[PDB]
Length: 271
Length: 124
Ligand SMILES: Nc1ncnc2c1ncn2[C@@H]1O[C@H](COP(=O)(O)OP(=O)(O)OP(=O)(O)O)[C@@H](O)[C@H]1O
Ligand SMILES: [Mg+2]
Image (cartoon, rainbow over all chains, first blue to last red; front, side, top):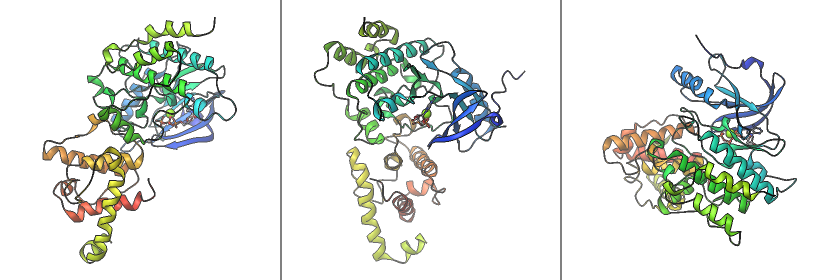
């Protein structure tokens, strides 16, 4: 039997285009009474093998059991769809990146920033209980969405597929030094993800894009080969400094697990 | 087009060469790497891959290509990968074979770089 036929591409209402980039395009749309985004993956040298892989990789993103994980609602198989396509619920505030760096109406306060950190840590702790890990899931501020009640949610629609831009990294500033250089199979993936969270902490503290003045190639090559790191921000609380420093330990084995830092972040909220 | 520029214009050819020496050094110097000879330092494919990332806005994970190729086969793979990235950037499939770059066919080394310069002129 064929378990899942996926979502009918013909049923999607494409309203307005939000982006076109190296992956394909992103639209705001509607489907069966849902406000959604539609991610259209435009893949060179599409093949039956890659289409098979898309349909096996997509179900793992359909995670409906944790408030800080944003599931892929479903996917359109290609064929019969024009391109491999995935849909997710529309998050009114966009990405964490948008909220922190492109917010024209308000600046989120630091209590909200701490809550974002807790939300992300809870979602990553849950994802780290999956066996095996979801492959090619990178944590960065573009791959977390902010829902209508300001809940931060890990974006499963931003997990790269096996065929999607292999050999390229468009957000290296969040990637652990070892993960810039070694195959994922030769890295502790959970520890590499904690480095990404440490960079998120830095981002929430500075309200700056990490290494904003450098190109992605410069970032990856200098972090991997020249010991380039974000500078600890000056005059923040010792408690935040110590947390940032241990999550960004040069030794992957010494970085904490997400379920270890969730109680620290809980105690950092307001009584 | 480019055949006439190589074969039947030595004065113009050297105006384009110095250009390409400035062009690739403009970008690779950001990685503390210098290009002093257009005809032999792109042959192993490494600087072509690094250049493509600098020009199209991505990092290439080091496990995705051979940073220090140890064989003719590895350089050919690097160059082929760089040509794939060129095609991902909108260029049509380059006319030289990847082995021609690894064998320093200057008309091929210059043609690849010429099409890179032409396309990525305004890039900083
Ligand atoms: N579920 C969503 N709800 C609302 N806006 C979203 C949602 N997902 C993405 N967006 C928005 O659309 C923009 C473009 O995202 P897009 O996925 O196309 O590019 P990207 O995340 O930078 O790269 P990539 O293709 O690798 O995922 C985002 O910056 C964000 O503002
Ligand atoms: Mg995305």
